[PDB]
Amino acid sequence: DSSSIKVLKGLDAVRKRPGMYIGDTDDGTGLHHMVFEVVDNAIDEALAGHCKEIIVTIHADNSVSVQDDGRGIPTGIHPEEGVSAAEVIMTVLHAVGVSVVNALSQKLELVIQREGKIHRQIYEHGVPQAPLAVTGETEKTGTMVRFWPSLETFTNVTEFEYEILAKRLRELSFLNSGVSIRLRDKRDGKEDHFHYEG
Ligand SMILES: CN(Cc1ccccc1NC(=O)c1cc2ccccc2[nH]c1=O)C1CCCCC1
Image (cartoon, rainbow, N blue to C red):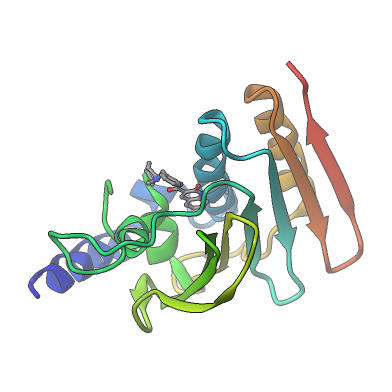
């Protein structure tokens, strides 16, 4: 309705002044902050007792993905906005927030494994191609977000550096005692694993 309007309004505002939300867009700090934001979302689910392992993969097409084995974002339709709760999370300001990463991603794939099913939604610059759809069956739970940073927004440093993710992810495992985080670089086979048990 007009909610499709306000979503676009907020998305506009983020793409207009990206540094204000994500960090400096010209020296790689914001670019990498895109990842830690998605990861911080998964860490929350781990701090609530539902996530154990987080898997961050740097893909060959210069996208990153974050996988967890938590509950899966709720997939039920929201009363105020008439779309899945998941889509509200990914698109509404203050639902930072992941919506910022979505708004500043040329493309974003969401995959949720929940109550026996696998749901999927693709976004372009924060805009869904379609409503969250059920794609298939599954016996595991979790959320997977894969994003391709918007090349309009990020300048100079537009490729992820393994060592920056590696350092910060170790730190984040230490800051949230008990979480396991794995980092895979599919470009050259680099791999690492972080976990501080208390
Ligand atoms: C509604 N969720 C919490 C919640 C409630 C019930 C079941 C699963 C969750 N999980 C989540 O929302 C959730 C969101 C998420 C987003 C990006 C990447 C990984 C993610 N992993 C998650 O687990 C969050 C949404 C963002 C703000 C806090 C509440």
